[PDB]
Length: 197
Image (cartoon, rainbow, N blue to C red):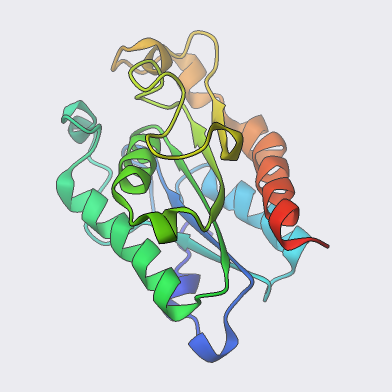
């Protein structure tokens, strides 16, 4: 299932405890792409189907390859889309713990959105996972204004985007195992750290 709009479709009277917002890579389908579904499945196993809402960044985020060369690593329209989703989560479910993630252009999108986000909302994101982080070198493996302890970066050796080049090499397409194990493990651990249980 490459398309998930649980936050947009969800009833505010029955908010999930955890809301995951994820940005796909360049040219990927739906709003979750290749890695999102694996992460989602594992989050559901941990918090139960009604305990977590999975929301992909769709709308104006078209994941156009060329946009990864723009100043922030994605388009302004895409940043506004993801910011809007964080704002919707905050208003619809004030008590939900947030988590986020992004792959390739989506990782730059996640970082830019989190950087611009109002601190009160940003501080609700218990953990963020980034795969093939295009701004890894430039930002020294961090997301501006966001704590290192809540950030996990998956950058493969040989993935040129992690060392400053906008070129797609084989290691950039090899994040499947991470999305199936360590990424959801990290997100689950970070949520439990603040929510207990």
